[PDB]
Image (cartoon, rainbow, N blue to C red):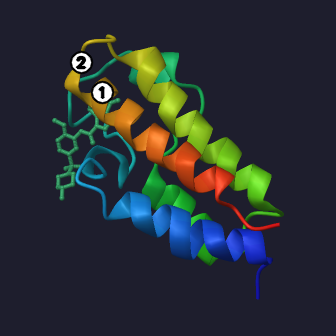
Amino acid sequence: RQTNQLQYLLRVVLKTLWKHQFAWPFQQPVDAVKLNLPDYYKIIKTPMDMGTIKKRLENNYYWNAQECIQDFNTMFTNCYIYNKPGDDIVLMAEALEKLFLQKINELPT
Ligand SMILES: COc1ccc(S(=O)(=O)N2CCN(C)CC2)cc1NC(=O)c1[nH]c(C)c2c1CCCCC2=O
């Protein structure tokens, strides 16, 4: 049994983002070896993705809403830091982040 906010972050926020057309690059960790990105783990000290966030939500890892929001923010900023600002992945990230922020301000008290 989790707090109302955490429940909403899983059943509303994560689930809406997961079903989005641009969720696919964000549903699993970046496999930097398979994708030939030798400096990825050197630049990204804390990889994060929606698949990892989901499991944490489902496992009661998070103490409260803000910790989950922190993970989401890390996922987005990792993408902006690593890629070039015109890359497709970055415009997908921006799109997904605006919806996220949208659903976050809709969060219950
Ligand atoms: C060619 O890309 C892929 C090929 C296959 C796969 S995948 O997991 O094998 N899978 C996705 C789900 N689909 C159903 C099956 C294929 C992922 C990816 N890539 C990503 O995810 C991804 N995500 C980020 C955030 C970045 C990247 C790579 C871009 C630069 C680093 C970067 O920032």
Answer with the quarter of the image where residue 85 lies. Answer: top left
Per the image, label 1 sits on a secondary structure element best described as: helix
Query: Residue tagged by mark 2?
Result: 87
Answer left or right for 49 relative to 61. left
Depth check: give the residue in front, 59 or 33: 59
- 35 with respect to 26 (left or right): left
> Is disc 2 placed on a helix, strand or loop?
loop
Identify the amino acid type marked 2. Answer: Asp
Q: Are marks 1 and 2 in contact (CB under 8 Å)?
A: yes
Q: Is residue 22 visible?
A: yes
Q: Nearer the viewer, residue 14 or 31?
A: 14
Residue at 51% across / 57% down in the picture? Answer: 52
The answer to whether the beta carbon of the residue marked 2 is less than 8 Å from any atom of ligand 1 is yes
Q: Which residue is mark 1?
A: 91
Quadrant of picture, ligand 1: top left
Quarter of the image containing the N terminus?
bottom right
Task: Estimate the spatial distance between the alpha carbons at disc 1 and disc 2, rounded to whole Å.
Answer: 7 Å
Rendered view: 67 above or below 97 = below
Q: Quadrant of the C terminus?
A: bottom right
Residue 65's spot in the image, x, y percent?
76, 59
Residue 61, percent across and down? Answer: 72, 67
Q: Which mark is residue 13?
A: none
Relative horizontal placement of residue 31, taking residue 69 as reference (left or right): left
Q: Residue at x 42, y 64 (%)?
A: 16
Q: Could you tell me residue 44's position as x and y percent?
A: 52, 24
**33, above or below 26, in the image:** above
> Which class describes the residues within 10 Å of circle 1: few (<14), some (14-19), or many (20+)?
some
Structural crowding at the residue carrying mark 2, measured as other residues with C-alpha within 10 Å and reported as few (<14), some (14–19) or many (≥20):
few
Amino acid type indicated by mark 1:
Leu
